[PDB]
Length: 215
Image 1 (cartoon, rainbow, N blue to C red):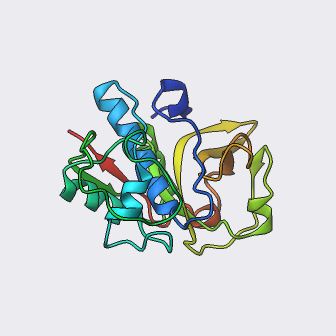
Image 2 (image 1 turned 90 degrees about the horizontal axis):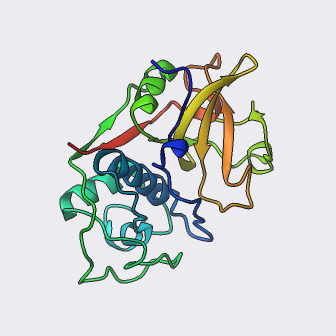
Image 3 (image 1 turned 120 degrees about the vertical axis):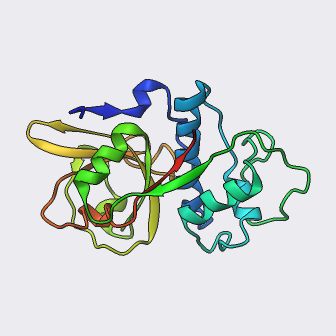
């Protein structure tokens, strides 16, 4: 099991995006994970449409929230998802485009053992993983750089993606991709302490991990 993993260095992670004024974190987290597994399996990194999920996943709640697993289920049932180029992000729920295309598809999704950072590390070593984090706190929102150590709660009020992990001067960390643009955190990313005392993980990051599968 690698001691260091960073999917960004393997060309499997897209440029940072911005969800803006829409409660679509669930869609951004799910899409990022899908974009990555597609690259890992097919060799091509394609930017996919978060907007399609906001408009077409009727099991989710548009800009009022949703869940990454709902998103994976939609992509599977729909037979795929369109590109960002053909179905651009508008940050508001609109009509689900009737003639959208199914460019990238997935075969299913796996739910990682809950509240177990070791199990989560194993999953991240294979591909980026979608997770929830408590991100309403001042410490988290004003994060600029370095390894974030809290404080924060465990509410599942935000969805992000873990794109790597490692250790720096004795401190274990997770590399987390946020969807608040490049002007937030460290060029859009946040390094969060890993292997903390609480089984739920820092800010509850280990509570509900899942990732898409593609044979």
